[PDB]
Length: 11
Image 1 (tube, rainbow, N blue to C red):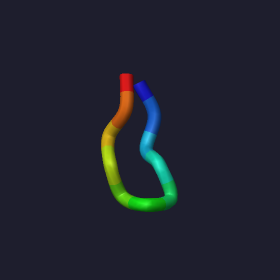
Image 2: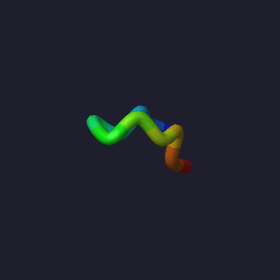
Image 3: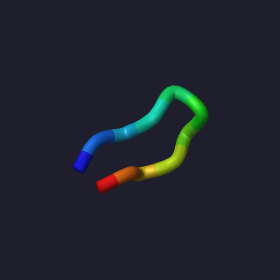
C-alpha cells in the first residue's frame, strides 16, 4: 500500500 498525492491510501 502507498499514499497518493491526492491524499487517498491505495493498495
